[PDB]
Each structure stands twice: as C-alpha cells, then as structure tokens.
Length: 126
Length: 128
RNA sequence: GGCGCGCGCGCGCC
RNA sequence: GGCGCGCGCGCGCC
Ligand SMILES: [Zn+2]
Ligand SMILES: [Zn+2]
Image (tube, rainbow over all chains, first blue to last red):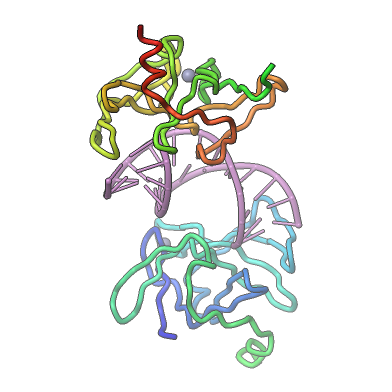
C-alpha cells in the first residue's frame, strides 16, 4: 500500500523507506539501496554467531553525529553482505499525515512485505 | 502434609516475606497477605500518583522492612472497612518448600497455587 | 536479526 | 495493585 518512512528512534533522522525493505524467511528485514549505506556505520560484533542462513559479522548504528543508535546487524546472506534492521529501533511515519507509530516486533507492523530477491540486486548491481 | 505451600522471598534481599497459605485474592486480581507476622516485614510511605481505582483507595507504597534493602513490594489500600497491603508477585522469589526450587513470576496469572478468595468473615474471625 | 528472560526506571488507564 | 506502553543496561537459544 502507501509508503512510510523509518526514522531513527534516538535522533529521529530519516533512515529509509518501507518501499526499500525486503523480507528474508518471513522474519528478517534488510534495506535495498546504496543511499541507505550512508545512513549507518558498521562495527565488529562482540559475539559473532551464525543462525538460520546468516553469519553475524557486526552491529550497525546511526551514522549521525552524537547518535549512534543501535539499528541492528550486518550479515552474509548467500552471495550478499547486507544490513538487517530491527523495527524496535525506528519510528514509522505515514508520509502523508505525519502520524508516527512505534512497533516492538516486525509482525505487529503491517505493510507490504516484499520478499528478498537475489535477482533484484544483480539487476541493480550489474 | 500439604506440599503446595510456598514461601515468598524479597527479590532484592531474599528475606522471608510470607507464605502462599496466608495470601488472599480480591476480585480475582489483587493479592493481599493475612496476619501480623507479615506486617513486621514491611514499611510504608505516601504514594506519588495514587488513590482511587477499582474499590481501592491507594494510601501508600510499601517496601521491604530491611533497612538495607527497602525493595518496592506494593501498596497499602483502604478496601471497604479494612486497611490492607496489596503485593506484586514481581517483587518476590517463589520458593517451593518441599523441593527448594525457586521461580520468578512477573504476573500473578502466571503463578499457579491454590488461590484462596478474600473473605470479611475471615478478617473478622481473626480480629476478635 | 528473530525469539525468550533478567536488572534498573519512567508514563498512561482503571 | 492490575493492565498497557515506553527509556537504559545485560544474558540465553538459534
Ligand atoms: Zn540517530
Ligand atoms: Zn528486602
């Protein structure tokens, strides 16, 4: 349906749009685009682990000045290296009303959840 | 012997608070404790945001009597003609007497024991 | 990241 | 007190 914005919960800076969100295995969420990479920084995860289909390499934080709010992790998924965000760190804002809402779990936030597609990235990267 | 009775220990200092046998439930939601033995285990002071709700008149927040703990245990209310303490299971360690196993419950609804309903006749029979 | 629990605390409703 | 929500810190399992 309509498009929404994701704002950092701590500093409230624009993070990304739900239009660029892709769902893996119906439970993990990543964001497509090179623009988004400017929004977060990556750093060594203290306790690296491997679950489901990923290999946890680091945690990502808000790229902003004094913010650095924990946004999620960065992993290895198949032939890719992608960030994985937790809805709990962001504020969802309806673009046409300014109405903001907070979700604790991805399952409680109902929007168009488009599945992650490897062919969708090799088309934008090649 | 009844091997369902449980001890309630202050979560912060581990001191004995009371037994589940002395616990009475008001309106299927609020839990209070019977007897003076329990009255010696806590202290109280006026509540910040309180008073009227349900059939209660929140008259104070109660804490663990141990001067080196003072853990929050609940509140004291005016219920009908009585003045009673109301406790939150979230503040205690549940220890099963028969096996010593300790458990932590965040909600009364999760703690399963023989829940005896509060009854004024009981209150009275013990006052005279 | 998902799920779960713990510790400390704030706010609303009754 | 019950119920809901949020803030900060930590742990377990995958
Ligand atoms: Zn931020
Ligand atoms: Zn204590």
